[PDB]
Image 1: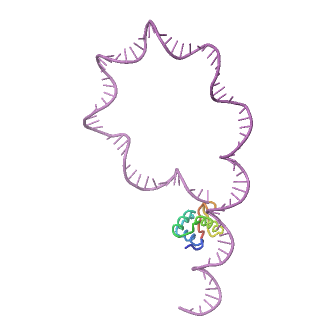
Image 2 (image 1 turned 135 degrees about the vertical axis):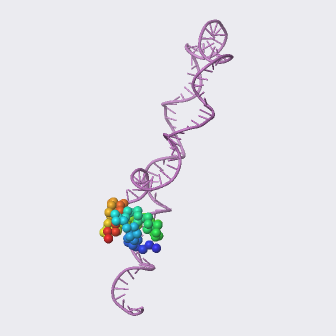
Length: 74
DNA sequence: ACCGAATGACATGCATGCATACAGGATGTATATACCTGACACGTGCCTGGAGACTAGGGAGTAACCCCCTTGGCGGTTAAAACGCGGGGGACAGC
């Protein structure tokens, strides 16, 4: 029951509205605990952020690459 | 509000990532084989030093006593141990 990775990621940030930006783990724990994702879930989430930040709609407030915190950037 | 055109959602086609098992094939290792001899094993001296027997005289082992200092006990106070806890920052994991 997993649609395209665009949707839960933005939903997860909406769940915990950190103004400083959500740290990489905060999304990772919730979406796997809440929904059901494939055996290689964590790998897909990391590059999901990586491609998502390249699209520019999300802002990494702290850290470099995937290791930091990210923000919806409205 | 259903009918079309259009479009988002749903369902799957397509391509890919990734894992995995293999089989190869290469290399290193173990086997498998002769010869080889420095080198352990006697072997033969050869003597000196360990044993026998000797005396002598002190140090260890006894008894004997003692007293102190160890152990025991015996309240009183109170300083320190025990407990609760609120939390923050140190460990730690991940990229």
